[PDB]
Image (cartoon, grey):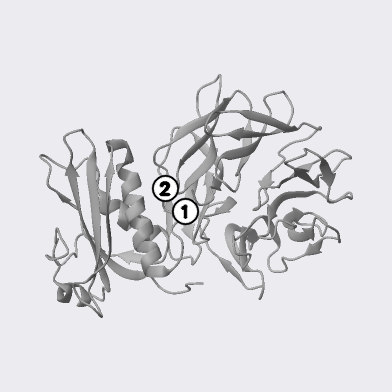
Amino acid sequence: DSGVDSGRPIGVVPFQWAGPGAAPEDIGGIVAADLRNSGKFNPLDRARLPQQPGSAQEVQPAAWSALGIDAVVVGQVTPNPDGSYNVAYQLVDTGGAPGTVLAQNSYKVNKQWLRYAGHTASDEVFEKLTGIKGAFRTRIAYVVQTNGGQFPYELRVSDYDGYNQFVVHRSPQPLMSPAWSPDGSKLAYVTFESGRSALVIQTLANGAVRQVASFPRHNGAPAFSPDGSKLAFALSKTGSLNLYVMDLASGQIRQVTDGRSNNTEPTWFPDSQNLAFTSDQAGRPQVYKVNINGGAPQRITWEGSQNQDADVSSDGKFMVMVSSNGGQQHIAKQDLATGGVQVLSSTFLDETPSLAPNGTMVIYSSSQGMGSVLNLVSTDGRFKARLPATDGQVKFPAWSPYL
């Protein structure tokens, strides 16, 4: 819903490093990358910075408004004797009230939390300048297939931008489609470890695992309801996949769809009652919507030869999905009210899109020979980037809720 050329230009100056040598991290670089990733901003190339002020007072507004820049982010990174660091940023106005500090904060963090300090600065500048909750301190879950033979599959979690990865679960068999609990503490996912498909929910903090379902099938594509009370997923035995809803408090499972049609990849609407999902009911896959509390499925995608793997935004205003047309398979966004569709990505064979909690960015995977990598694309379509390559093929990314 930004629908413009580039984003709002903004000056993000490298942070001053008072400590000896060089800085342990490029905080300004992180803030710029974050802001840019959202498609909401176009940080000025470090090449064209008119100056590199190290403090708000050193900022000369005229130099920035001149280049069409409303605000400038300046900052300082200072080493503490205990080995930790002080990361401070000041958001300085270079427009209506030149030189005034719109926002500033300072954080004391260990080397390991320096990127977090950067993402915090980004979140603050972001919420202050867009009114939209920042998602820069969010994480993503995904599955990497390494080249190791014993446990090729690793369900991992990392910062949304690919850094600070950690393994949640390693498996000798395929792992797929993790899904975050709304409170960000658990991941549901499908594992073939038992030899056949199973749906589990693992608590990230202690690794605890809850068995949910095992009926005969393949990928269950789980999805937690926004309110935390249910988990929707697909089971395929009768010869076709159908939707089931898991009541998390009681464990009672109820079938939400029936028929010879393959109904899968459920995703929740904000009300925790309606699901959007993929069905082959009309031939090539299309996206349908159904209220778990009663009613028959309602096809909702009409544009495109095929649409699947939907992800409804947190505000229910739109959804992203994999849309195939003219031999191109990309992530597309569909307005849930007016039905307009906008193709976001342009990479090769885009799959499983997952919306950032503020709905400003989508993480998805694309094809690379026999493998695949993760990508980010802002929901306004302005920014596209590969996430940092890792030691394996990556699939099924899932963006965490706000943390």
Q: Is residue 168 above or below residue 400?
A: above
Q: Residue 3: x, y in percent? A: 48, 73
Residue nearest the viewer, comparing 215 with 151: 215
Q: Position of residue 368 (x, y in %)?
A: 51, 43
Q: Nearer the viewer, residue 319 or 390?
A: 319
Q: Is residue 154 above or below residue 50?
A: above
Residue at left offset 41%, top offset 69%: 130
Q: Is residue 372 visible?
A: no
Within 10 Å of disc 1 (Cα), the crowding (few <14, some 14-19, many 20+) is: many
On the picture, is 64 further left or further right than 381? Answer: left
Total labels drawn: 2
User: Which residue is located at x 63 percent, y 26 percent?
Assistant: 173
137 sits left or right of 307 in the view: left
Which amino acid, by three-letter code, is at mark 2? Answer: Asp
Local SS, label 1:
strand
Give the residue number, with chain letter if any, for mark 2: 161
Circles 1 and 2, Cβ within 8 Å, touching? The answer is yes
Residue 149 in which image quadrant:
top right
Instruction: Report whether 337 appears left or right of 88.
Output: right
Residue located 24% across and 57% down the image: 89
Residue at image point 17% right, 45% down: 78
Q: Position of residue 12 (x, y in %)?
A: 25, 61
Q: Determine which residue is flagged by label 1.
A: 376
Question: Considering only order in the chain, which callout, 2 or 1, is on the residue closer to the N terminus?
Answer: 2
Camera-side residue: 77 or 237?
Answer: 77
